[PDB]
Amino acid sequence: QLPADTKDAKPLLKEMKRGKEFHVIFDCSHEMAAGILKQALAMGMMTEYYHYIFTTLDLFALDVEPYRYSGVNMTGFRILNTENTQVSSIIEKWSMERLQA
Amino acid sequence: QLPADTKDAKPLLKEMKRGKEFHVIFDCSHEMAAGILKQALAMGMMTEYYH
């Protein structure tokens, strides 16, 4: 279980690494995925060995860049149908009004 | 040999990782050491393996 605070992530990952858990499933609002991935990097774990999975259905949202050359696999799940033209159009339109926040 | 700019580092480190060169000596004014180490990190080239 992830402890209460996000930045307490350290021991848990540390135990996982010591125990040599070479697969992981997550389940949490991607907002938690950000914290857990930053730890998973700074703890020197993003190596093509480990191979995460996410059930949080918004994996696409995360900034995949600073991890992408490392070589881990982050199979996820997305439903918002980016494939269709009109869907993407409406995404963009809503985006042009989304950024007022 | 490191190329002209530092951020150019990526191909070289790619070769080091591919051939599995598990040790290194560097040499640079540390200002180069910083960028080369950052690349060393984001390349998945910074673990308890290497030294």
Image: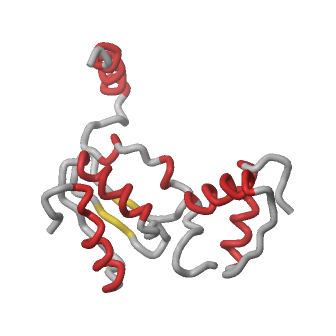
Splitting the image into 4 quarters, where does residue B46 fall?
Answer: bottom right
Q: Is residue B6 left or right of residue A29?
A: right
Which residue: 79% across, 56% down? B29
* Closer-to-camera residue (A45/A9): A9
* Closer-to-camera residue (A48/A86): A48
Splitting the image into 4 quarters, where does residue B41 fall?
Answer: bottom right
Residue B47 position in % (x across, y down): 53, 74
Q: Is residue A77 left or right of residue A71?
A: left
Splitting the image into 4 quarters, where does residue A91 fall?
Answer: top left
Looking at the picture, the colour scheme in use is secondary structure
* Closer-to-camera residue (A35/A84): A35
Which residue: 69% across, 65% down? B14
Q: Quadrant of the N terminus of chain B?
A: bottom right
Q: Quadrant of the C terminus of chain B?
A: bottom right
Residue A40 position in % (x across, y down): 38, 63
Which residue: 25% across, 48% down? A30
Residue A49 position in % (x across, y down): 45, 76
